[PDB]
Structure formats: C-alpha cells, structure tokens
Image: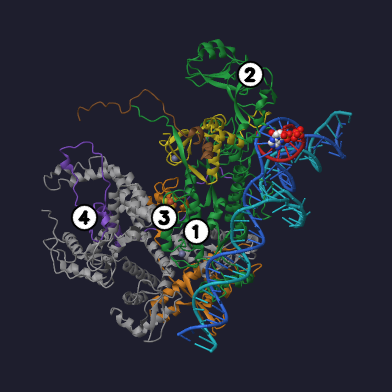
Chain colours: A green, B brown, C orange, D yellow, F purple, G cyan, H blue, I red
Amino acid sequence: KEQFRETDVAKKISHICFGMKSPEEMRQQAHIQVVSKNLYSQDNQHAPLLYGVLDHRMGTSEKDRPCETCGKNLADCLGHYGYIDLELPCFHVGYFRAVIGILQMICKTCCHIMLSQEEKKQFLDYLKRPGLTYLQKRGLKKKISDKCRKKNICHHCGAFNGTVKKCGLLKIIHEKYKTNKKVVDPIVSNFLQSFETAIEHNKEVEPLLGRAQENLNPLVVLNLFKRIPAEDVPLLLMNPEAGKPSDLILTRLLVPPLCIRPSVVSDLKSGTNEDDLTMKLTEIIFLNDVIKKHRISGAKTQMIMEDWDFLQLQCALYINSELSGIPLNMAPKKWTRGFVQRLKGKQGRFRGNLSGKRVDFSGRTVISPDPNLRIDEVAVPVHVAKILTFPEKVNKANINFLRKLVQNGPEVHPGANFIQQRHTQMKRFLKYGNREKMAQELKYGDIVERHLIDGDVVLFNRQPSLHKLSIMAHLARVKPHRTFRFNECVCTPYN
Amino acid sequence: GVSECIIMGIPMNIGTGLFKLLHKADRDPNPPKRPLIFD
Amino acid sequence: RSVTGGAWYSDQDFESEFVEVLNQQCFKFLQSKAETARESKQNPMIQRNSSFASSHEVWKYICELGISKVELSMEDIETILNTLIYDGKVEMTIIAAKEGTVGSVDGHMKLYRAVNPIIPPTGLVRAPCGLCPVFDDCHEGGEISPSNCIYMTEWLEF
Amino acid sequence: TEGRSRDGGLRLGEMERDCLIGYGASMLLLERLMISSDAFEVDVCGQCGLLGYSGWCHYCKSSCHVSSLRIPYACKLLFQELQSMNIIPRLKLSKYN
Amino acid sequence: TQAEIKLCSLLLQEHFGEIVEKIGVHLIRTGSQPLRVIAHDTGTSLDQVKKALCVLVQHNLVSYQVHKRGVVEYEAQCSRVLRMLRYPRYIYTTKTLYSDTGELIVEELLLNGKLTMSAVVKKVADRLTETMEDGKTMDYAEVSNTFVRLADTHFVQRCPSVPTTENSDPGPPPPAPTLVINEKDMYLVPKLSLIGKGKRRRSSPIPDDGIYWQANLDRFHQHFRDQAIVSAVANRMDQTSSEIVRTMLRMSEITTSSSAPFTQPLSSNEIFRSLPVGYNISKQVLDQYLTLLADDPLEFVGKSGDSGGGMYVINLHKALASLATATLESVVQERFGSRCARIFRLVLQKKHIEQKQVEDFAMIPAKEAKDMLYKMLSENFMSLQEIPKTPDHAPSRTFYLYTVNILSAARMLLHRCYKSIANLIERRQFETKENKRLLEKSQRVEAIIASMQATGAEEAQLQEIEEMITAPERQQLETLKRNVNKLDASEIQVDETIFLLESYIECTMKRQ
Amino acid sequence: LPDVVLKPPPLFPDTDYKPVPLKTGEGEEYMLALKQELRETMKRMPYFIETPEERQDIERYSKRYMKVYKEEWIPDWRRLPREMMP
DNA sequence: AAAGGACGAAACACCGTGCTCGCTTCGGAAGCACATATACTAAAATTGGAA
DNA sequence: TTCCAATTTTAGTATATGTGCTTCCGAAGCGAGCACGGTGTTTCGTCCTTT
RNA sequence: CUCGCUUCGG
Ligand SMILES: Nc1ncnc2c1ncn2[C@@H]1O[C@H](COP(=O)(O)OP(=O)(O)OP(=O)(O)O)C[C@H]1O
Ligand code: SF4
Ligand SMILES: [Zn+2]
Ligand SMILES: [Zn+2]
Ligand SMILES: [Zn+2]
C-alpha cells in the first residue's frame, strides 16, 4: 500500500574528505554548459541569456526571478553549478607546484616513478602503518622527492631524466638534452643534428640550438599524467580515492552558482553591478571562442601560443588574482578579486564570515553610570527592550502571563511582537487582528516573541576585548532613559 | 577541534560539551520478551 | 617566383584542382610503369630499374599531357613527386649518374617508383572509438557513454 | 548587514569568540554564531558527499542517500567556493548517536 | 594505466566472475600485498579471497613471493591479463601451424593455465572422440607426438617447478615453496608409456605428476612479429622476398633470444640450401634479392659481414619501428584524411619543420595545413620544440618547430586502443544485458524442442514453437546477434594494432 | 570576432569519416566463433566461481531435486602456499 | 513674410576590440622574516699513473 | 704493485629573491560607477529659390 | 546595492 521511507534522521557531519574532481565528474555534477560570452538578451527587458553566464538554471540572484532548475525563490535556492569546456588544457595554478613536484618524481618517458623496487617496497611499508598524520605525509613526500631527484636514469625504461624547473610563468621546462662537458651521449648528438632542415631554412636556429630543452606544455603533461600507473599513485602521497594525477591539469571549469556571484540591477542607469568572477568567466569564454576561431582560420603558431598563454593567465587570475611572475605587458590593468582573495584576508570568509560574524537580536548604546543597580544587573532602555524580543514557549506555567503579554500588544512595554502557532508555522504580527482572541487561543507549544522584560539574562560586552571578562551575562532591568546603565564597580573588567 | 566545530555549526567538545546527558526516565532495559510458540 | 607568381598561383589563388590533377596523373603514370615492370618479370634488378622513373622523364610525360597552359619546369614536377612521396604512395632513390638526358643534379639523378603501402589499415580505425572526436569525454556513466553512443549505433545499423 | 544606517546587527569578533571559548559556553557560542546569524538547512548526499537540492542529488541521479543537515550559510558558501576552485569537500555524514 | 585497469576488470568479470575480478583489480591497482591486507581492503570474506587468489595463480595471472619474516605477498601481472585477450589468435595460429590436435592442446592449456601432460592428452583425446564417429577411438600416441612437436618448437613450456623438499632444507615447511624455474627441463616432455582411448561421453599413480605445462606466449608473440614482418615485406617488394625473409627468420628463431637489436647473421649459401625447393631460384637470384633488400631505405635486413659469400643479418627493432610508423600514419590517414597524412609523413621525414616550410613542401593551401597541424597537436600526435631566443620563453620571440615523437605517440595510441576495446566490450555487455529478457524467452521456447528431443518426442511440439510472439521478435534477436558478432570481430582486430604497438614499445626499452 | 552560440554543440558531433569495414575471411570468422565458444564454455568451467546464493526462504523436499551439482577441480596444494587450503 | 524639395549635419546605436593619441617606462620598495634553491665551493674519496 | 696526484661527486653550507604577515568594534558621507572610437543610420533643421 | 576613499568616535 504505502512504502515506508524515513522522513528525517539526525545526521551529524563526521569528517570532511578533501579531494579533486576529474573533468568527467565536473560534467556530471554540472547542470548546463556555458557557451555564450554575453550576459543579457538584446531586448530592453535584458533577460539573462540562455546557456550563457547568469543563466537562471544555475540558481538565481534576484528576488523576483526564480531559479529554473529548482522552482524556488532566492531564499530557498541552494544554487547549481555549470561547466565550461576549455579548448586547450591549462595548468591549475593552485596545484602548479604539485604538478612540478610530480613531474620531478616520475619518469618523463614511461611515466613510472623514479624508485628502485627495494625503495618502493620500503616506502610502501612505511606508508602502510596506521595513524599516518598530515605532517608525516608531507615529510614522506619530501623524502621521496629528494630520493627521486637523486637519480638521473630510469630503472624501468632506461631513458634519461634531466631536471624539471619552472621557467617564466606557468611554464615547465625539462632539461632532457643537457650539455655534457665530458664525452657526449649519442642521444644529445642525435637531437642536435636532427635540426638540419630547420637550420637550412632558418639560420638563426643554429646559434640558438643550445638551451633547446623539452617544453612541457599542459597537453603533454596531461598525456603523461593519464599514463601514470595507479600502483605508483600512492607513492606520490596522493590519495587514489580523492583524485588522480590527470585531475591536476584542468580542462573544464566549474562556473559557480548565481548565489556566489550576486548581480545588482541598478535601474537608475543602463547597467548592472557584477562581481569580478562573472567578468573573468566572460573573458575565459571569449578566449576559448577566439582560440577556436584562430584554429579554424589558420593563424600563426606564435599567436596560437600567445592565446594559449593568455587563457592560462586568465584562468590563474580567475583562481588567484594576486600573482607575481606576471609579465608587465600581460599584467592586469585594474584589480580583480579571485577566489583566493575572497577566501584570505581580514574580510575573507574564514575571518569575516566564519570565525566572527554579525548577529541579530543585538543592540549597541552609549553607557552611563547607575550605582543603584546590583552588580549583576544592567539597565536597558525601554526603546531597545521593545525591539529585542525573546521567544518564550507556551507551557502550563506561563500561560496566564503570556496571555497578558499578548493582550498588551507591541506598544505597551510588557508584551509581545509576534505569535508563532504550534501546528502551522505562520507568524502573526500582533499590531493587527484582535489581540484578545489571539490571547484566548494560545495553545500549549506556541511561541510568543515577548519583549525583553526584567530578569532576562543578557550578554553585555565592550567591543575591544582583551580578556574573557570583557563580556559578561547580566540581568536586564528596563528603565525609561536611553542608555545602558550598570553598577560602576563593574567598570574595571570592561575598562 | 574547536575552530572546525565553530565553522561547521556543531557544539564544541571543550567546555559544557565534553560530557553527554542522560534522561532518568522510568524504564526497564531488556524487557521480558513474548515467547514464540511455533519455534 | 617566390614573392609573386609561381606555376601554382593564378591571380593570388592557390590551385588545389591543378595540384590534385597533377598528383593523379603522375601517380597513374608511375603505377602503370610499375605494373609493366612487374609483368615484364625479366629480372628483379631490371624490374626495379624499369619501374623507376626519372624526374625528367615524368616531366616530359606531363608536358606531353599538357593539362594546363602554364609551363611546368623540371623542379615543379620534382616538387609534385615530393608531395606524392609525403602521401606514402611513391618512393624516390638518388642514384649516381654523371651525365645524361637529365643532367640536373651533379652526378646524381632521382628515380621515382610507385610503391604499395606497408600494411592495410590498422584494426584501431575499424572501430568507431578509434575515430571518435569526443573520445576524451567518453565515460561509463555520463552524457557520452558507449551504451548510448551514436557512433556505434550508426556503425552497427550500417 | 553592517551599519546602523542599513539597520545592521552587532558583530561577534574573533576575540568575542575567544572569550566565549574561554568561558567554555559551547551552547551559547553555537546559538550566537549559527542559530541567530546564518542558520540554514542543506541537503547532503551520503553516497557522493556532495550537496544536493530539495532532497535530490543531481550527481548521483538518486534521492535515497540525500539527508538534511543544519549548517551555517557561510560554511555552505565556503564549500561551494571550494568546489568551484576544484578543491572538492566531500562530507561523510553519520547519525548523531 | 587506468584504461588498462578498466580493460582488465572487464576481462576478469567476463572470464572468471565478480568476487575474483575484484581481487584481481585490487591487486593490479595496489600492487604486491599480503593476503590479510587484501582481504581487509577488499571487504570480502577470507575464504573468497583464498579462492580468488588460487584461481588467479592457477591461470598464472598472479605470483607470490616471500619477504622478511616469511610473509607471502601476491603481485598481479597486468600484461598477462591483457594477453588473455589474444587467446582466439593463439588458438587460430596454432591451428594454422599444426593439426587441430595442437589447436585443442593449446585451447585446454589456455583454459586451464597449468596442467600435466597426461591430463592434457587425456582431455584432448576425450574432446577429439566427438569430432570423429563410427566407433573410431582416439589414441594417446599421436596426441603425445603433437604435444612433443609443440614442445620442441617452444610453443608449450613447463611451468616453474617446486624444488625438492627433502634435498633443499629438510625440516620446517616454508609458508611458500618458492617455485624456481629451470631451463634444462624447460621443454623436456616426460616419458609416459601409458596410452588409452578417449570416452565418447556415454556417461554410463600419475607418472608425470608435478610436471605442469602452460602456453609460452613469448613464442606466440615472436611468431606474430615474424608474420607481420613477412606480410609487410610481401606488400613492399614481392612474395619472393617475403619467402626469403621468412626462411631467414625461421633459421633465426632458435639461435636468437626474444629481444636483440639484431639476429644472428646468416650467409647466402645456407639461405639458399635452407630455402624450400618449390622455388626455382638460383644462387645469384638469392644474392640479388639479398643485396637489393640491403639497399632498401627501410633497412629490414643488413649485410654486417662479408665472409661466406653473402653474409646478411635482419634488423628486428628497425622493422618494428617501421611497422609502428606505418600504423601511426594509417590511423592518422583514416582519422583525418590523406592530406593530413601527407602533412604527418612530411613532418616525420623532416625531423623539425615550421609552418611556412610545411606549406611550401606539401602544396597544401594555408588556413588548412595550419588547421590540420593544430588538430594533430590537440590529439598529441606531435610536439612543439619551441626553441627560445631568450630564457623568458615569450611566444613573440621564439621559434616553434613541429616534430613527431614516435614513442610518445605510440604510447598514446596504445592507451587509446585499450580504452577502445574497453568501450566495445562495454557496449556488447550492455546490449546483452538489455536483451537478456528476449534471450531467456527464446532459450525457453528453443529448450522446449531441446527437451524431449527423441524420447517421447511427438511431432505436435514443432508447430507451436513459432506460434508464440517470439516470431516478430526474431528480427531484434538477429540484430543483436549480428551486432555482437561485429563487436567481437572489431575487438579481436584492434588486438593486432595493440600487439604491434606493444611490441614496438617493449623493444625500445632497456630495463636497466 | 567569433559569433555567439545560442545552443550547446550537439552531444555527438557528426564525422565525415566512417570506420573501415572489418576484415573478412575464413580465419576471422573462425576467430569469432572460437571466441563465442570460449565465452559459452568458460562460464560453466569450475574456475568460474559464481557468487554464493544465500538467504534460502525455506527448506523443502524438492531441494534434493533442485540441488545444484557440479564437479569441483582440486588445486595442487604442493605448489600453492599453505594458507589457501579450505 | 509664408513656401517646400533636397542637402548637410549632428547625435545616437553598433561592432571590432581591448581601456594609454604613440607603443614606454617611472619610482619605491614599507618592515620584519622564514622558507626557497643556485652556484659554489669545497673537501674528501676513489681511481689512474710514476716509480 | 702501490704512493701520490687529479678529477669528480655529492653534500653541505652560506646569501639573497619570494611570499607572507601587520588590534577590536562603531559611525557618518562623498564618488562613481566599463568604454569609448569611430562608423553608420536616422532625424531634424535650414542655405536658397517660390509662392 | 557593491566597492573603495576620507573624517570621526572609543
Ligand atoms: N585603538 C583602540 N583600541 C582599543 N581600545 C581603544 C582604542 N582607542 C580607544 N580605546 C578605548 O579607550 C580607552 C583609552 O583611554 P586611556 O588611553 O586609558 O585614557 P586617555 O585617552 O589617555 O585619557 P587621558 O588623556 O589620560 O585623559 C581604552 C580603550 O577601551
Ligand atoms: S564509446 Fe562512443 S563516444 Fe566513447 S570513444 Fe567510443 S565512439 Fe567515442
Ligand atoms: Zn535552484
Ligand atoms: Zn622511464
Ligand atoms: Zn550523490
């Protein structure tokens, strides 16, 4: 007849498993693909474009237009992601160092890690112990990196492995064909002599034949990371369940929901206030379209690589808006807020919205002395007490008291501002309707938002807080004046 | 840790959250079981 | 001829049709010569030598054909044969010949012969996944999956 | 919001949180920083560890493992920003028992 | 090796089951591990772990080694699990080279992994009694003759043998017997005087005990490489050259190992005398063939000596590189057209080259050669050299040179082939799963005929099998069958490209 | 400047090159038939360990009639390490 | 002074393109501070060679 | 055959370029908001020549 | 509204 499904379980978060998403998983998670670089439609209504940025299938950011994925308003919409396909793979700046590290660990030809079998077994045994800590993992990664950089030839395929270093910005160079002051290897001589046709057609190649090492563009790095054996992935200290080496190079961008990027319709002019993320995404999509157009139209290799570098730089700025090795001609003109900027700083999420955040049901007033109050009491102005409400639950003890409070209404000081019914959660404003009937219909379990009355425990604080006694709980007593008053003997803790 | 408890919006382990409270309800643990006739 | 003109460029337009017809005619001539050499079966050395065609000889044959009005130099046909070599259908060897009816390169003459491909098309290209343009995005569970793949649908239906 | 002109509320700064921690008042700290400021109820899929909507997980295309969970809204914003940064936070839920 | 892991998972699930494919995949993904940690990580019972490990080690898919404190650790051979896909080719090539008796021998060896010679001859005789009829019995003598003929040609090899316990450390038994391999008795068949006749499935102490045999896949790979080289040279020059090089490789088979840059050199006179007499060829014709092949710009063979008349050697690694190059150019041509293949061959012959030089040498108009070059760059078919004028590596002040690296492109193509075969198997399994309902319905209606075939078999059950609604569904059944046939054929034929690429990749490694 | 696109590109973009037709001959069809035979025969092989069915509803007199019977191969424990005996 | 056909201009969308007309061009670092990796350099050890 | 001399190899060990930080609220207000360069198209007003 | 900048208060 009816299937038994559990309504709600008191689920508690146990732990957070950090990780990475492969390009396939990004498409699976996302709802739509963003391909239009424009934002609004041509018509004067300026509705957001379809399959472009600000599409309301990615949530909503305006109180009037609901989300298209889930038919809910701005208050209830959790937001939904989209995905943007990149024509050319680009290095993830946040993982760039990691990429370099991994490129140092493994062979550049057979993709195996630079470790002997005995050292492999030893490191696996050391990693297999239970209770491995984050510091232990970092130390093991450092030791393995040192011992891998000790070697120079491959025990698996025999290919030479030179040094891998960061040249320029977001570019990796592998010194495969290093100069040998001693007798030269056949490989380097063959590589040097393979430039015969290029030298014949371009003489300038010959003076610059030196310093011509292997360049690991994101395509080659992605291809190499796709061929790393899964056995050696734990030896890179990377959790196989969390992610894979191929995930370090991004080919899809998860464009965030509209809730992260609010848009303000400033109808006073013909424009809107948009955050930096939307403009960065617009520029990235424009660059993808430009690269595709250049590939179609047969452009030079120099400008193709320039557009690829521009796309990499734009992705890095979208992730982190404060980089160092930016070329002066490639430097941004103005200042944009990347995700790192939104996270770090005194106004970031952690310090400005997570560790310490603004609250309601609070007030801030000038103080004046009052010696006639006990040291555990504080005088609250009548005006503030009429605003700061306490939700008192109707029980068998305070029913006759809450009835009188409801009868008084929101104007007389001992009284209430709202009534929340037990069965239906529809709040009732006490300024309207017959208050006597509402008082006569007070059921047990109803919530009455009573005014702050005498005896209520109230926190009292001086904002420059040095020690724990800078904030204390007092008992509120309502007084006709407009200042917070307390006994002067309590001045010394608050300073 | 305390900071992650604050971020996740869960009661922190230190302070009043170290212990757990039980209700001294009128009860009988391991109540008598109705016998099975067919088995 | 480099900065302007050229036997291929006509009014700042590359002639794809002209080069295609040149490739077809040269390859047909080389294939016919190789077929005649194989059918001769007189001796393997003589068979291979007769299958060989000089650049001057094929240039004279092309001039006899006279497909286009523009005069084609010997090195023009040499470049056409080089493109045919890059197509994997003909093979060139530089032999030692001090002087003769060609006399082009000092002591060396280039002989071209139509040669069969090494192997038939590989097994990889016989499957749609080997030619799929969205092979990177293919995944077991997702929008692009082998279970619902259109390419194999058309391929099996065909 | 921030200011009096915008009818903003007062701010529990980092040191206020530190003083509340020093007192050991866990329940009041939770009520002030979660219940009274940015309380929210999200839907988390217990299988993939990602955030769902309206009791449904689009990633898993299922609704069996989706469970409601109380959380500060700023934490949800942080999780979504981290997901956009390819730093995927996967939540392994459990019963409160 | 994620594609390799997926393909191994599919093969093990199709061939052995589920509780065993999980163990195989875990071993491949995590490497060598002791039994208890495998059981703990997999999450299944210890008995199932033991059954999976023993059934895997029976087919030589995994091996066990001893370590410190006498712990036994099991490591899987991913290459062997991938070689499992070549079983139809192994059976077909042993049926081509020998009689059907050898075909059945190799089939039993592959289906059982390890077997004794008495067991294999008994099974082959039992199966062959069904092929013939009219009371003819299958004797063990001819089966043993075919088995020893396979053994001397190195197609079947003895499994590693446990050392004698009494002579080697008599006392406490080790956790693992530490099987070692001896090349003296590697291909020595035992003397088994017992003979017999296979039973006709009427359904109404071992002299060679401890001597286990298996299929030597290395010999099959060497034979396949010889076949590929012979076919290539036949396509190049003539069938006469193919026969000449086939005879040279046949002579080289025994005297050389499976991995050498060059084989043992041969003289002209021994090639002439070893050639089949069916070819009316004189000594000077053979010398002409040898010297004209020696001048081939493919360098299949080489002189490498003057003594004994025409002294010649065969270049194996050069031939494999040429075959890999041909495979790469063929896949490029079939995926992007003949013009793109022209560009690919141009940039292969010229080691480094630029866009303008490519356009000048290919006679391909601009905006199309550049587009095809960018397309091939997007698929890792070539890499840019990017010689910089300054260490800043700015694009405006550097030269970009196109260059095809055969090794990296071959590895990419092998990975793509692995994923392609995985996708083909997935599609076949999906179609089978979705049509299993009609499969069961048709199995039932055809088993109505299959049941009571002769006993109590009235004719009134022949006009009602097609009476049910399965008749209009037979078209869907036929489509399913032809789709499965085509998918299996393509899966088999991609294995040839996989073999060529894998051989080229293996022969370019040093394993130092 | 590149044009703006109103709809995302098709999920499976079309290709003007089609896969080469499969190789044909007696040998290739023999390979196909042999592979199908191996599929059909190696599932019934005792090496193919099936998932153990469990949770029998009831015991019945028909169980003995429906009891699945299959010959089991005996591993050579001399080569196999000692830990895998049942 | 009241006309009106054609011409000219001027003011607002519009797309190629990237906030600077032309390609340049400065200064200052803000301080206290723990990382880095480069380049060096140096010694010590091992192997080749005179006696 | 073996003591000295030379070369290499790696390792360690000092500076010097990078990245990273720098009190807690609170309150007003003033600015200014992405663009602008030139190009085209449309609309409107008036230099003569006409009642 | 967002952002920055200043001036305050303490
Ligand atoms: N920047 C600030 N940070 C924290 N608290 C502050 C700050 N500025 C002012 N205050 C508050 O004001 C108080 C400072 O007063 P204090 O310095 O003790 O007397 P004063 O200002 O020197 O007066 P006299 O000059 O002595 O008459 C203490 C503190 O709570
Ligand atoms: S399954 Fe379909 S989409 Fe995936 S690689 Fe094969 S043909 Fe392409
Ligand atoms: Zn929504
Ligand atoms: Zn290697
Ligand atoms: Zn989920």
Residue highlighted by disc 3: E3
Which of the two discs, 1 and 4, sits closer to the camera? Answer: 1
Taking depth in this image into account, of A417 and E456 the one nearest to the observer is A417
Q: Amino acid at mark 2?
A: Val
Q: Amino acid at mark 4?
A: Trp
Q: Quadrant of residue A326?
A: bottom right
Q: Amino acid at mark 1?
A: Lys
Please provide percent x and percent y for residue C47. Answer: 41, 79
Marks 3, 4 in one chain = no
Residue at the farthest front position = A489
Mark 4 crowdedness (10 Å alpha carbons): few <14, some 14-19, many ≥20? few
- Distance from mark 2 CB to nearest ligand 1 atom below 8 Å: no
**Residue at mark 2 to residue at mark 4: CA–CA distance:** 91 Å
Verify CB contact (< 8 Å) between mark 3 and mark 1: no
Mark 1 crowdedness (10 Å alpha carbons): few <14, some 14-19, many ≥20? few
Q: Chain of mark 1?
A: A
Q: Chain of mark 3?
A: E
**Residue at mark 1 to residue at mark 4: CA–CA distance:** 49 Å
Residue C83 marker: none
Residue highlighted by disc 1: A143
Marks 3, 1 in one chain = no
Which of the two discs, 3 and 1, sits closer to the camera? Answer: 1
Residue highlighted by disc 4: F73
Verify CB contact (< 8 Å) between mark 3 and mark 4: no
Q: Is residue A33 visible?
A: no
Earlier in the chain: of badge 1 and badge 2, it is 1
